[PDB]
Length: 224
Length: 224
Ligand SMILES: Nc1ncnc2c1ncn2[C@@H]1O[C@H](COP(=O)(O)OP(=O)(O)OP(=O)(O)O)[C@@H](O)[C@H]1O
Ligand SMILES: Nc1ncnc2c1ncn2[C@@H]1O[C@H](COP(=O)(O)OP(=O)(O)OP(=O)(O)O)[C@@H](O)[C@H]1O
Ligand SMILES: C[C@H](N)[C@@H](N)CCCCCC(=O)O
Ligand SMILES: C[C@H](N)[C@@H](N)CCCCCC(=O)O
Ligand SMILES: [Mg+2]
Ligand SMILES: [Mg+2]
Image (cartoon, rainbow over all chains, first blue to last red; front, side):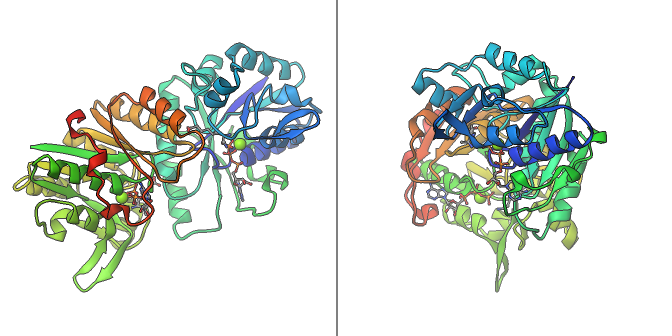
């Protein structure tokens, strides 16, 4: 079944918004979809335990009705690097558990999207990063680029490292994190030339609740 | 004579503030110093033409009295990627001119610091990036890390790419861009373990005019 890992040029660049757009587009194409956020930090308390907003957005945007834990096995309240809070709370993040969770979603979905945490190299322990897991799984990677000053360097750095790891950069998504700026078009042309992967689509600047905006239309799944 | 290229995990992470600290420390050590900002964007008009604040900070912090043009040959008013504004204004950025400017400073200084623009991969033309020039010059690189969420990934990405290019990562500087946060110490430990270069020093959060604060004391030049 189809599976993709979604990373970003940094934390807060739009991985979640783009992932929802990707999920909506797959559903529109006829796929039985599932979003997976194996490791999450920055979560709120609820009667059922801790709940992460990214995990909730991916869960809502999946065509299948999924249990929270199936979408997000590891939930930490504090919004910091996974490895720091995991060590402080004494709750190890295990590659095997993250991989088991992906297989579990594949029991019912034929199109799975995996959102990472932060950027490419976000640590999970003192000796293991998210990149290590993505490489282990041999997941094709989709790069979400928040269009802003500094994004060219970050996109280039991330694309080079992904390719070096022997992984496939399946595509990139341009996300308009802010209203139209002076050099928007020039940045889009530069990004298009430099990222060795197809531009899947561009998500407009959607001020109000973009996680729940109908954004699937901005993604051309046939380029993936 | 000694020469170092200063890059950062992104634009606006403190390359200029750290460069001033580095320059002050070298001067304290007895060196005849010179800061060099070959390419600059985001500049103000003056009676003498355009003037960039980074270039002005490096000029002020050099032990030698340097002419503005010697410090910054290429000055663009608009604060965007060098390649975009250079093309729009029809003023090509030439590797040869940038290299000639470095040699010119070396006529009088025995310790030269070169501040890049933006991050590692900032484009200078449609086919040439700053990284290309740094590689051509075989300059040892100092990585400035603005201590904040997302910096681990960026530091790791930049360090890997620099090493891959066959260049020497001479050291890194931790810059406190914001007041003390919850996981400061844990981030410093993670950064120290992961960056394959000596931590040269840490610049405290200095709210008021940090470019002109006495920061040389935070750098241990003997580790460089
Ligand atoms: N296209 C957009 N238009 C308007 N706002 C956006 C857009 N994309 C993202 N945002 C907003 O910017 C913020 C960051 O986006 P998002 O949560 O998707 O990023 P992220 O990369 O998933 O971050 P994290 O590393 O926490 O997983 C959010 O508040 C989001 O609502
Ligand atoms: N240690 C610090 N304490 C307080 N403020 C700081 C500190 N370092 C940097 N700043 C502020 O943060 C901003 C960015 O820093 P700086 O100009 O040194 O970054 P930069 O990486 O040189 O950016 P550019 O890519 O434009 O060259 C500036 O307004 C600066 O005054
Ligand atoms: C305006 C800004 N401070 C410039 N001096 C450097 C910006 C370069 C950004 C390049 C990129 O998008 O990676
Ligand atoms: C709190 C934040 N939104 C997290 N979900 C992801 C942050 C990871 C940052 C890791 C790093 O410093 O590179
Ligand atoms: Mg997210
Ligand atoms: Mg600067």
